[PDB]
Length: 330
Image (cartoon, rainbow, N blue to C red):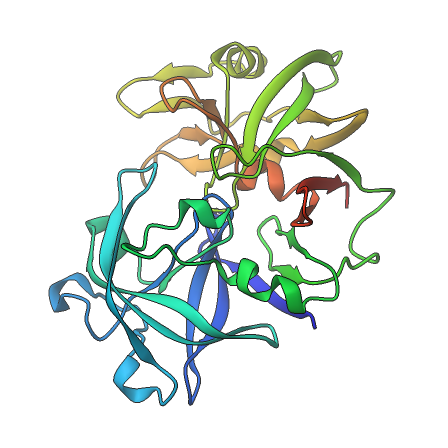
């Protein structure tokens, strides 16, 4: 089997992407944030504290004839931006882009933090990291991909995120029309539960390539590109007036700037992030200070190839017995 679904930016900045997901019988369609940096499929639901719901579409398990309470199971998760959610668990039928999994753990939120409430466009998350990170207790649950894998034509999914435009998540096949040139595959460590790999270096604008190993994770659920402070300083040094602002929480730059590209290495191959992808717009409405899309990972504890980087590529998440990651230009 295969599946194919369109993923759409939630706003004009590509702050996140939502993909429609069918849950239950009859189908309830929710727009979920597909997140290769976590491993829980959780949703706003009829059980979510009322004051914490503001415009999201909810899953109502009592209206699904295939929903069953997973007795005794609970979940609780915290994310890198300080947000969190928790609740109980149902199993139900879940379909993405025509690919159906029966008995998928659907984690129903009883509580969500303010940032989730405040974002009316995201109805929940669909985790696509390794199932070892799933938070359900006392019996850990598998991701949608893990459950689907054995049925797929090939044990893969691909992310093809758009810049200020829709893109595609495919399951079970590689669309050879969706990229240019060849796909370069690189080793993955699953030791931390992530799609963790090592980039071979970087270049700023038309500058020379610096060969250096940068360990990080391919994370569709993170907006920006978080890299070592040395790398990030080298980038922003090429933008007149750019500086790190502790009050804003990262590098800012004059909105009048033209940003240089940023290149990262995948083996002997190179992915070029155009400068415009690195502009996240005014820090507050009407400001002429703009927020940068490349930020320091110092104090995160891990480098993160978030959407800024991934949207410049066609990315293969290869879930074969020994997982790997593939990157192509597009």
